[PDB]
Image: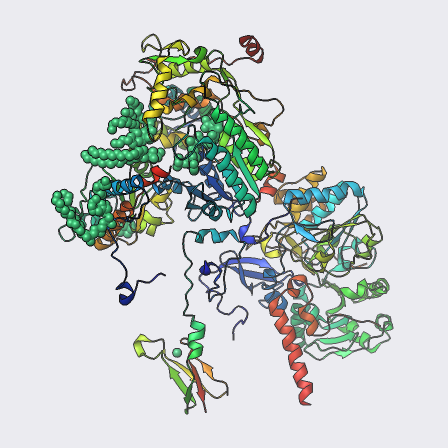
Amino acid sequence: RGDIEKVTHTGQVFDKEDYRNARFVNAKRYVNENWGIKLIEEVPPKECTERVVFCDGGDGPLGHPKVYINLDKPGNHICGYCGLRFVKK
Amino acid sequence: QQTLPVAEVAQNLPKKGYSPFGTKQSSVAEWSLARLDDLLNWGRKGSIWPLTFGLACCAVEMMHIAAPRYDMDRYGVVFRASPRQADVIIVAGTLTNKMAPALRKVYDQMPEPRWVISMGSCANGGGYYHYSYSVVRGCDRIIPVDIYVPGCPPTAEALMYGVLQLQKKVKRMKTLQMWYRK
Amino acid sequence: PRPLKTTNPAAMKRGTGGRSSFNGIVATVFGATGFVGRYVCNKLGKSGTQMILPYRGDDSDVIRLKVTGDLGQVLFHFYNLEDPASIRDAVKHSNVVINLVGRDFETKNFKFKDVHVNGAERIARIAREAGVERFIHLSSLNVEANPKDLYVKGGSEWLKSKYEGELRVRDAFPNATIIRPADIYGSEDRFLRYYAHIWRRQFRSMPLWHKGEKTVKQPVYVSDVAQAIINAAKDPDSAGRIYQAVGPKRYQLSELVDWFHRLMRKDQKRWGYMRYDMRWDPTFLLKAKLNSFICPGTPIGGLHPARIEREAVTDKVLTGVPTLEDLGVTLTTMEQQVPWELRPYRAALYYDAELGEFETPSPPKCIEARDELRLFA
Amino acid sequence: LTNKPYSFVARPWEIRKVSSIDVLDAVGSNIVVSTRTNEVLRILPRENEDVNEEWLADKSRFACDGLKRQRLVAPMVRMPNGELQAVEWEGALIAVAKAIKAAGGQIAGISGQLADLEAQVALKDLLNRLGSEVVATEQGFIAGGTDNRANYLLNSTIAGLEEADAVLLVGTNPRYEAPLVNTRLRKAYVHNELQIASIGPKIDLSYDHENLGADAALVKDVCSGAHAFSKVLEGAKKPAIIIGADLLERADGAAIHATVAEYCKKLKKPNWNPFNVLQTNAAQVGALDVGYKAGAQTAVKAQPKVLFLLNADAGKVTREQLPKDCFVVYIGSHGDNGASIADAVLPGAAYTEKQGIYVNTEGRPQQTLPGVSPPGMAREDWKILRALSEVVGKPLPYDNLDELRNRLEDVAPHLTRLGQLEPAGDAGAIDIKLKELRDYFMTDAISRASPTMAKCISAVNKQQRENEAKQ
Amino acid sequence: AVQQVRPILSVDREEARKRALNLYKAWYRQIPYIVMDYDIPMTVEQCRDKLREEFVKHRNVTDIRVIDMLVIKGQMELKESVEIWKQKGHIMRYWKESQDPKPTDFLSKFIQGV
Ligand SMILES: NC(=O)C1=CN([C@@H]2O[C@H](COP(=O)(O)OP(=O)(O)OC[C@H]3O[C@@H](n4cnc5c(N)ncnc54)[C@H](OP(=O)(O)O)[C@@H]3O)[C@@H](O)[C@H]2O)C=CC1
Ligand code: SF4
Ligand SMILES: [Zn+2]
């Protein structure tokens, strides 16, 4: 079926000759469709004015630890935890 | 994962019907066997008699399934002692090496058709003592297992859900319908 | 230097050989539920093989094999022998195919034509299409181009089909291995039980053809046969050759049956065992003919006219065809195994005998090669 | 500051530490190979005052990627058409055995760069059982040099250099050839007030040093005492002369080796041995210490019908120089140019998956330990040769490592005493490779296969391209 | 290099030799009962060899205290076998039947892999 040849977001797939596909003849291979690498890429960056800002995952105690980011460089800056991007202009 | 049908889509689907073989049998002989096969399954499905194994601290939650809150007996499940009259074995607990020959024998003495349920992590894959020097790493090493109920211990409802899975597994046996093709 | 079919490291041999190891063999045992299958599958599971076990009937029969292997190393695949689409699914990833499909009698849906020759060909033909490297088939040892009957007017059909099935297998899969066993035994069998059953007797007796004195047999323990199948599977040198699977010793059928009934404590002195000559009593042949007709699923006590003809024919081990000793198997003698096979069939087993109250039975006397010349004139 | 290639791969508590040694460089620095679930994550320096000093050169630190690329997994054999196909072991060893019987004694072997002492000894014994004696190495060397163990070692121990007072570097850029030694020289330069001089192309050592010039006749000038720096060496309380192993391989090397080895005896002071040869391969010292001849031309000159390339992935040998009737059998870990010529490739294990003895430049024998199982159907290097004798018919005296080690114990007793040194007493235009940082990273098969070292080469080149662009 | 110690069961090698033989007696007497009361393939002659085979394992043992311990453990099994506390599986455990032979020759091990 389709799922056998589908390649997961981690980049793994059994070769069409690999015997290990035998395990899927009577079952399915759920490949998640909501790839995190693309959903985070979709969200646009946040323009700021201050020189340093903080992201906490967005919901305080339900988010990730509060980390501060420095925006001096031109390129928009990624948060280590949540992956959100920040930029000063 | 196959998700459930939407209401509007499901609003058209025909009623499922009881038998999992449908009423689409071509011949009379096949159809009679199909219906007759349901009669067997209805019988075995109704009255599933565990063996009262109760090895370890899953065993306590195997009592509360018989307690008034959940009442295994409502489903025709009746505990029994002798493996001859017992139909199902619920291996609930940590099957150590010293026990292992005893479970094998007790399972063998059970007459066919016999189904095994594995309760909790201990009996599933060795659980919390997986690496111990005197633990059989899962009862499936010793006897075939038909349903795996995860948990530690599984909740009473969790085991109940397991038992109903065994009823459905029993409900769809093709003991007769496959004799015809054989 | 045989080319390595695939260099993907995940599909290479790994480990110490225990259950968690891997042989690099992806087998497919057609007919794993049968008597031989239980022993082939378990021996594969020890090595670390990954096996697909197609099963035609309900899962209940085959579910017991899941214990043989390790996690993810045993997979079941429902299939219908007539439908090739079903079979391709189970042979499209395999390196080895083993064909233990056959029956001792005919059915309403499967005559010997459909199973032994047409069925086995279909499994072999599909295997070649998929690209299976190895193939293994079973056949009788006395297989002949046109076997003559000995006591039953239609008792040779089973062998005729087996011979024809053997050729079509070699036709479809020219480098197929063929192992030709003879009177396999050792538990859940139809040799040591077919002689210990109630039906076979007549109230205490044993109708044997010529009293069994003109029949010579070389029974082989089933485990040795299973070891042969696997050893042939691990080796490519064994491809495209015929192997005869026979025991180490030859016995007259009269000599064997006497020895069983001594092991079973069913001696003539007390129990009342005695040997007819099957030709004298026609009642016995009626029992088989009645027995075959009445029972829908499987004959009771393994008794039916086809099985009778197997008993009458003496094993004919050809000279010059390789034996399991060529495959490295060390054959177990009957004296080693049979005394433990028949412990649960012993008579007066409720006794709780004191030590020595039952004397150890005398062993059977094999038949020397020269004596077989005289015995057969 | 943290390792970029290793980023996020694992955590400390998970790791199972495996003390080993490095082989990409001759210094033999001690190592702790971090392993987790049958894979080398990183390589860390193990403290060892006498050799390592807790530092570690990059080529040792970032070779762990090379062990996961271009690796040989299955035996391979040249088909009649000309391509290689993978085959089973029983088939391969039998295929090679046919060549050996048909070769009829015209056999030769060539040890490589990453070769092992134990594997090298097996290769020697196997060829002696066949009667052949053409057992060489890849690096060339002064003829007759193997007679005295002091002729090819750092007689002044690695630790001993840091006390040095006047050092003469002849055709040696230790900053790249063996950085851990240079780290000791700079330590002397900072603290012990070291005076340094060079003979060869201008280079930078990370510290001030005089360049006497690249002329060949200089070395005889310094020896003759006429040269100005010659006064410095004869006055210092711990003079030392370091000569690159590359120069000795050169044709002139024998004369150069004689003068300085003659000059050192004048400079020789109580408990100090000025003469010092700087090696660049972990295999070389062990090979010469066992009885190998030197130079890959010792094997070409025999015109052998069968040749064993044991980890010999240098480009020194080429399929043209071989007789047109030849059978090249390459026993190694990484498929490279060495394998590209081979007629029958037998996979070996890399140093992280084989317990083997290596002899560092100063003479210390040290033992690796197997942190990782070898991949695919790879086996240890000596196991193959031990097995290959069976299919040829002359079983070797030993069937276990301890049995093999005792054979070394009989050839050279000191080789057993691991982590120790035996003093060897007396010893009886220059141009250099490896003068640029760009040339430092790509010197070995393991390094040459490293994805990380590809980035470093591009990074160094990238900066140079941009720098000239701005100007 | 000698030290003073507390004896286990015996004081002299001769007494230790005497105790060990008794353990051989009791086992050799017991084999006929074990065959009857256990559903196992092995016969008396085969078992009586296994008794001989294993008493030979500890061929080079010299220390009396070690010999005492072997006889303490050796006796314990016999009581657990004179009784049928040991099950059918345990008795056959003395043969290692399930484990198939592992070849010893170098060439076979190399081809088979580690
Ligand atoms: N005494 C002996 O056993 C000897 C061995 N042989 C041959 O070895 C082979 C295996 O031996 P044995 O185990 O005793 O045979 P069994 O009768 O015990 O089992 C045969 C297997 O083949 C399956 N089978 C039979 N017919 C079909 C069919 N139409 N379609 C699919 N599967 C079918 C059966 O499946 P299921 O039961 O689930 O229906 C069963 O699993 C046999 O073919 C036999 O002829 C030859 C000479 C002597
Ligand atoms: S699985 Fe958990 S609850 Fe069940 S016996 Fe084991 S430890 Fe107790
Ligand atoms: Zn964040």
Q: Is C164 positioned to the left or the right of D257 in the image?
A: left
Q: In what quadrant of the picture does the N terminus of chain B appear?
A: bottom left
In the rendered image, residue C334, in percent from the top left (x then y), is placed at 46, 21
Q: Nearer the viewer, residue C359 or B44?
A: B44
Residue B79 in view here: yes
Give residue D218's quadrant in the image.
bottom right
Q: Is residue A88 above or below residue D255?
A: below
Ligand 3 sits in quadrant: bottom left
Count of labels shown? 0
Q: Is residue B68 above or below residue B142?
A: below
Q: Is residue B76 above or below residue A85?
A: above
Q: Is residue D176 above or below residue B99?
A: below
In the rendered image, residue C153, in percent from the top left (x then y), is placed at 45, 18
Q: Is B27 positioned to the left or the right of D384 in the image?
A: left
Q: How is the image coloured?
A: rainbow
Give residue C318's quadrant in the image.
top right
Q: Nearer the viewer, residue A60 or C92?
A: C92
In the rendered image, residue C291, in percent from the top left (x then y), is placed at 34, 23
In the rendered image, residue D139, in percent from the top left (x then y), is placed at 77, 59
Q: Nearer the viewer, residue D319 or C249?
A: C249
Q: In what quadrant of the picture does the C terminus of chain B appear?
A: top left
Residue B111 in view here: no
Please identify the residue farthest to the front as the structure is shown: B27
Q: Nearer the viewer, residue C287 or E107?
A: C287
- Residue at 42% across / 44% down in the picture? C79
Q: Is C359 positioned to the left or the right of D1 in the image?
A: left
- Residue at 74% across / 49% down in the picture? D80
